[PDB]
Structure formats: structure tokens, C-alpha cells
Length: 286
Length: 287
DNA sequence: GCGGC
DNA sequence: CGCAA
Ligand SMILES: O=c1ccn([C@@H]2O[C@H](COP(=O)(O)OP(=O)(O)OP(=O)(O)O)[C@@H](O)[C@H]2O)c(=O)[nH]1
Ligand SMILES: O=c1ccn([C@@H]2O[C@H](COP(=O)(O)OP(=O)(O)OP(=O)(O)O)[C@@H](O)[C@H]2O)c(=O)[nH]1
Ligand SMILES: [Mn+2]
Ligand SMILES: [Mn+2]
Ligand SMILES: [Mn+2]
Ligand SMILES: [Mn+2]
Image (tube, rainbow over all chains, first blue to last red; front, side, top):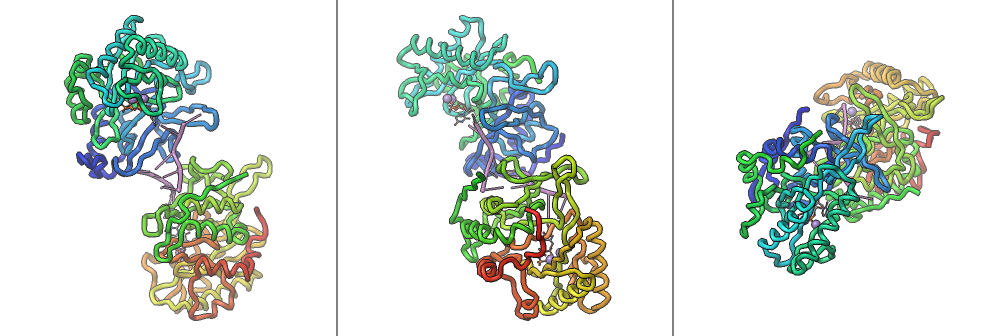
């Protein structure tokens, strides 16, 4: 399981001058905290081999040139069959870094070993994700107002909620399901939460997806629980002009009106101090 | 009903001549009927220039996961690892080669064969010898031909026919069909001996020995191209040089020309019309 | 040139 | 970024 880094000093984030070597070291540092939330899960990559300025691509299928030691499982979808890599070692993330795969994306479900035979099919969703996407001119004080409303709705079913800023524009809320439930079921539940909130605070929340997002409201993206969709993984970098991170936050932080996204270097600092704030999210692991 | 969509039609791949992807596509469409027989049943190695002859290139042997399911494919087992190659055997296969910016197509001297009992394909014997003539420092294309002629006779003196093909590069290729096919090992044995009998017959102009440098004033007869693991630029293939030259089959009379030169895709097209396939007898069979 | 349902 | 030996 050697991974040779190449183009160490190649700048991928021109704005901040972030070389592949930083990124390699970043993913080396976040490894212990990150791995648990992507283990057992099919890794979708979004790659910027030529920096965040040159075009990028999504990649699901594991290339034929990908190192044999990587874990892999197949998903069967209407037309075609996709074999994804499963990242579950620090070396796996090393590969991800070398690959210039800034972003790692996962669904909310894990592969499970077939009782009799052995090899893996997609299993039930282990967690819900609430994908909060702010509208035009949507105040931060209010984005959290909503996140808190979601938390209080879920705790009224004995479910805990963890906020993670996306590294992008909005906010993600994860909820562990002690007893896993199929993605359709996950979708059903998320959808009911969204709709119950939309009703409880009409002026700030919408459950309905719109081709151009709605001004002044927060859109609760419940269909992110569809077993066929992925959400940016916790502790992943983003391919934005600045190397921000999908970063877990404490609830206390959400009370900050001047709340903002975090950079890879800052997250690193926090981990040292904090540990994995999402520790109880995926307390079982491949 | 295998389709190939051309993308980036007007994208110039040879800046010097302004030859766009669409020219190349059309070329391969045009050379298809004559080219296909010499590469059918053979593992296609591609050398690709997706950004013109000025941007870097790569060899590709393995058939990518992303390539169209309708391509033919067989597998070769080697040292460590296994390689599934594409087999080009229809104009559409060539279409794919063009869309792929795979200027060059390289093949070995052998074909896959259907397994007598089971069906699927393992490497078979070599169907033809190839003599790869590599001229040295200050070697006049004239004397390069005398050597080519000397090879023809040594071979005719065993009832074997010889077809010349200019590589589209610097030197010259000779193919000989083997009526009865023979393992590449044996093909190498045969070629090595022709080369050596030649080296002796004309000491001043030929060498059989591979030098790291290329020896001035002499023509090196590359016999080891008959090795089963090696490939030679396929006849009718484009080259990825500053100019869009081609591995062109030439008639013997042409080799007598001292001002004998390489040919461009356009010329090969006008030749093929008037000529048919000069190599028609080289591979009389296969898809 | 291609890499996502 | 990787694509042959
Ligand atoms: O075009 C898309 C859009 C979305 N997605 C998947 O859906 C997830 C959520 O899609 P979002 O559009 O909400 O983006 P985001 O949450 O990552 O960041 P912000 O909205 O805060 O700006 C993304 O993280 C990605 O995994 C795609 O794969 N492709
Ligand atoms: O580095 C190499 C060299 C050669 N080869 C393969 O073996 C053959 C060796 O052939 P040559 O190296 O002699 O080049 P050529 O005959 O194509 O062109 P000239 O000599 O006329 O300039 C080539 O046609 C190619 O298929 C490689 O695959 N890689
Ligand atoms: Mn979002
Ligand atoms: Mn969304
Ligand atoms: Mn040569
Ligand atoms: Mn040679």
C-alpha cells in the first residue's frame, strides 16, 4: 500500500497557493477523524487535476489503472453497473490526494457483506442528512434559526443532530439512526421533517425544490436522502477558489451571526484541540 | 448498430498543416477498406495525441472501461499483469480510433485465434515477417533501397514474397506473408538469420546488431521486431510527426527512385483510389 | 479524450 | 491524473 506523491509543488488553489503536498498532508492529518464517516461507503470523487481554475469532472467508476489494493464494491443501476472505490485507510486518502480528488462525496448508506456468499451489496442508510441551502440574501442568523428548529424536531424522536458547514454556501445536518433504515424510508422521514418545519415557520423555510432557489427562504433539501445521491463528505476539501472544508461545528458556534466557512489549515487546528466532533455519528466501522 | 460521435471536428492536431480531427476522421473512413485486413484479429496499440502533435502523447494498450461495448477485445497474459486489447475490424472501429485522437495504430505480427473447443481468443502464431529497416547517420534513401532489394532476393530464394512500406517516418518496412504461419519465436529466428546472412553479403552497408547509438553509413536490419511482444506501426496508419505522414505501401519500382520520400495522408488517399490495396495479398483472410 | 445516473 | 512494455 505505497502511494507515491507526484507534482508535490503543483499549485491547485492559485488564490492561496496550495500545493498537492499541502493537500496530501491535510488528508494525512484528517485521516483518523474522517475515515469513519466514509468507510463502507462508495466514494464519488470530484477532481481538479489542473487546479481549481481548469475544468473538473465527477468520477464514480474506479479506473482500471487504480491500485489493486483499494476496496471496491459494485452498485447496479438501471443501465450499466458501477464499481466504486471504498476509502477506509489513510493510504486510501493518500490516493485521493495524489489523484487531485479535492472533493470526496458519499451517500448515506454502506455496503454490507452478504450473509451466505461474502461480497457486498448496497445496504440501509445509517444516517439522515438535512441539506440546508440558503436563498438570495438569506441571513446567517436565520440559517441557524432553522438548523435549531430541525434539531428540536428530531430530538422529539430521541434522535441527535450534528451540524457541519459545507465548505460552500450552506449547512448540513447529520443524524445517526441507531437502527438503520432503507434510503426510501430515510427520504420519507426527512421529507416529513422538512414539511413539518415549512409549516411551523412559513416565512423562512421551504420544502419544495425550485429551479431557481427562493429569495428570503431556506430550502430544506430532503431528497438528499435518496439512495442514489451523494453529499460532500465530512472533512472533505471543496474545489472553490479558497480551500474551504466541509467542517463539523459545535452547536454553540451556530449562534455566531458572523459564522463562516473554515479552511483546511483551520480545521487541522480544531481537530488537534477538538477530536472528532462527529465521533458518535458512525460509531461502528469498516 | 455501433455509432461514434465525432467531437471537436475543427480541432487542429497538426498545426504545421492545419489538419483537423475531421480530416483524420475522414482519412480513416477512406483508408478503411484497404487498412482493415492488416489489423483485423490483432491487438491494437494506440499512440494518442488528444491535443495535437505539440502536446505530449501516450501509448495505450489496455482498453479503457469507458470505451464502447461493441469493440472487439481479447486478453494477453504477460509477466505480471493481464491486458485486454481492442481489436479493430470495422470502419466504425477506425472511426473510434480517430475520435480518440489515436493518430498512430500499432500491431504485432500475430493474430488472436478462436479456441478449438471453447471459443474465446488466445494469441496465435505470427502470420507474417516484418523487416524494420532503420537507416543510420548520413544514409542515402537510395542505398536504403539496395538493402531492401537484397532482402527481397534472400526471401524469394525461399518462395517468399516481399512488400515494401515506407514507415511515414525515417526508414522503411518490409512485410512478407507466411503462407503457413509460425510462432513469433520462430519468426524471430528466421528474421535474425536473414539479417545475418545479409550483414555478411554486404559488409559495408548493413548491420544486424542493435547499437544504443545508430551506426553511421550503415542500415540496421531490426530483426527483433518479430518478437511476439513488440509492435510495428500498422500499414496505412498516420504518424504523429510535425507533418501528417503515413505508413504507406510502395511499389518496388518506386524504391528505385533516389528522391523517394515519405507520403502524406492526402497522397495516400489519391493513391488508394488509383491503386487498390497493394498489400492485398499480405493478409488474404481474417475479418 | 475520458472520467456521474 | 493516468493511459506500454
Ligand atoms: O450537481 C450536483 C449537485 C449536488 N451534488 C451533491 O449534492 C450535495 C449537496 O448539493 P448542494 O447543491 O446543496 O451543495 P453543497 O451542500 O455541497 O454546498 P452548498 O449547497 O452549501 O453550497 C453535494 O455535496 C454533492 O455531493 C452533486 O453530486 N452534483
Ligand atoms: O519506443 C518505441 C520504439 C518503437 N516502438 C514500436 O516498434 C517500431 C520500431 O520502429 P522504429 O523505432 O524503427 O521506428 P519506425 O520503423 O516506426 O519508424 P522509422 O524507424 O522509419 O523512423 C515502431 O513502429 C513502434 O511500433 C515502440 O512501441 N516504442
Ligand atoms: Mn447544500
Ligand atoms: Mn441542495
Ligand atoms: Mn524503423
Ligand atoms: Mn527499429
